[PDB]
Image (cartoon, coloured by chain):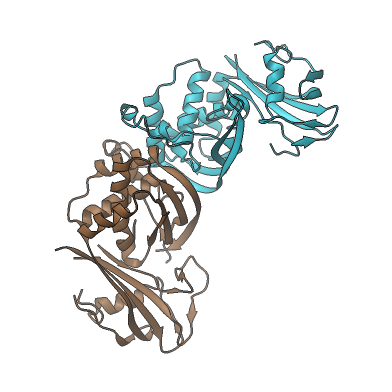
Chain colours: A brown, B cyan
Amino acid sequence: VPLIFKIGYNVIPLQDVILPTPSSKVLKYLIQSGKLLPSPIFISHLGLNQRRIFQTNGNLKTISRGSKLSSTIAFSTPELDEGVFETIYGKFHITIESVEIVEVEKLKEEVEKHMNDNIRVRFISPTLLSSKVLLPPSLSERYKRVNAGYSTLPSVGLIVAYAYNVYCNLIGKKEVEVRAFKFGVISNALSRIIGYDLHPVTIVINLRKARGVMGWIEFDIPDEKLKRRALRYLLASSYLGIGRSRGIGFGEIKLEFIK
Amino acid sequence: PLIFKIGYNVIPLQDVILPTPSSKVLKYLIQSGKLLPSPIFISHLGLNQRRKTISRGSKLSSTIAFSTLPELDEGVFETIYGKFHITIESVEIVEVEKLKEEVEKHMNDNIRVRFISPTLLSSKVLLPPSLSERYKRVNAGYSTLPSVGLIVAYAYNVYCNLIGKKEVEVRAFKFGVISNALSRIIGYDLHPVTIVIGEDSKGNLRKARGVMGWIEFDIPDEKLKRRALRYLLASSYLGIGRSRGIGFGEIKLEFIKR
């Protein structure tokens, strides 16, 4: 039976530390060297006071001994330990805050609770969605030279199209560009936007920079069948993140349902 | 066909209580044949460069725009809302063909669209026309966060009416879908607004929810940009979206050098 794991870590530096860029490198180092988990993967930036530490670009961030940093790792389809770990960035006490295991089928069931609820998507970390996902695939060649970049104001259609793609990979089915496109186009046509607070952000992936979006958007899809699909897909993205560079912590979303 | 864009100075000779929308004042004049013999746009009245109880002497401004010659006078006009001194601040006469020529000056410029008055764009303009019947019952309302595609789609429609050609839903749809796919959004400050549009058949107040603010963007495909500039340029005279004849959907178009 295929599953999604979402582990919440507490990460406490035992000495004053300078976090790497991106700050997800700390836990990535651990995982790579086989020290944290044996290895559709998401490794968050380290967070503090409900803000992720990502570099847009000033000086590097100092964290004092004892600060409670948090992290999330998420992946599909593995036993997990904690304790004091040594790293090139310093020594860290890593304990587990939470463990969520969701069966892909149980996602469909939670959708039903929210059929009459509005949808709030929050971009908790800068999110990088490519606009061309809503280009009709038959025109890919024609516009091959066009560099649209990442959307700094993504439409509901683009968001859910990205979610549908993540969902397909999650359930192990090949994503189909045409279904994604059609789904997003129709969603842009029919969605109702209730409110939003969006803004551009420029982030560091010498330096290589990218421009995406952060903030939140609240909306509804007033077609039962289309809403049911969107909720399912969004729910999956809420575990694995969305858009480019999720494995490094970008595209972190939090999904909220407003009664 | 030509486009006329007249800027009026509108000075109430007595303290006045403006109707809702405030464009009703000049609309009354035009309808009764008093301001012009008669693709039309009548702005809301503006004060201190922003679109209520208005004191005697306040310098309100208005803009009226329409397509085809000039037979326009000035002076004191009587209205159910009071007496007003209306003079002409400016007249722009632009040939529809000269629009195509100004497009070329801006091929390398970014595009800033500002919604100066609440703008009411229906999202369903980007619904594939073949699905209109299927989603007949779905009420999407007006977009409170319109995408570049929706904006330029609406512009294309206005342009068609301007040059007297029937708007084609399918061309609008395709043009907006492709524009959403390829546009680059540089910056923005948008927000929802819920406003009173006017009365209805029965006299009940009607509300609507739309957008105001600005959005800056580019279309990095030469051929598509050239089309979009032309259509946008036309919208910058005639406004955009629903209820332009009543002053909604007023846009100002700015080209940012790079």
| Identity of the residue drawn at 60% across and 24% down | B245
| Identity of the residue drawn at 72% across and 38% down | B49
| Identity of the residue drawn at 48% across and 39% down | B143
Q: How many marks?
A: 0
Picture quadrant of residue B87: top right
Which residue is nearer to you in this view: B214 or A220?
A220
Residue A223 picture location, percent across and down = 34, 40
Residue B95 picture location, percent across and down = 59, 18
Q: Quadrant of the C terminus of chain A?
A: bottom left
Which residue is nearer to you in this view: B138 or B122?
B138
Which residue is nearer to you in this view: B130 or A116?
A116
B156 with respect to B74 (left or right): left
Query: As drawn, which residue projects farthest toward the left?
Result: A1
Q: Is residue A228 above or below residue A18?
A: above
Residue A170 picture location, percent across and down = 22, 58
Q: Is any part of residue A164 visible from this angle?
A: yes
Residue B27 picture location, percent across and down = 68, 21
Q: Quadrant of the N terminus of chain A?
A: bottom left
Q: Is residue A166 above or below residue B96?
A: below
Which residue is nearer to you in this view: A50 or B149?
A50
Q: Is any part of residue A209 visible from this angle?
A: no
Q: Is residue A167 above or below residue B89?
A: below
| Identity of the residue drawn at 38% across and 60% down | A253
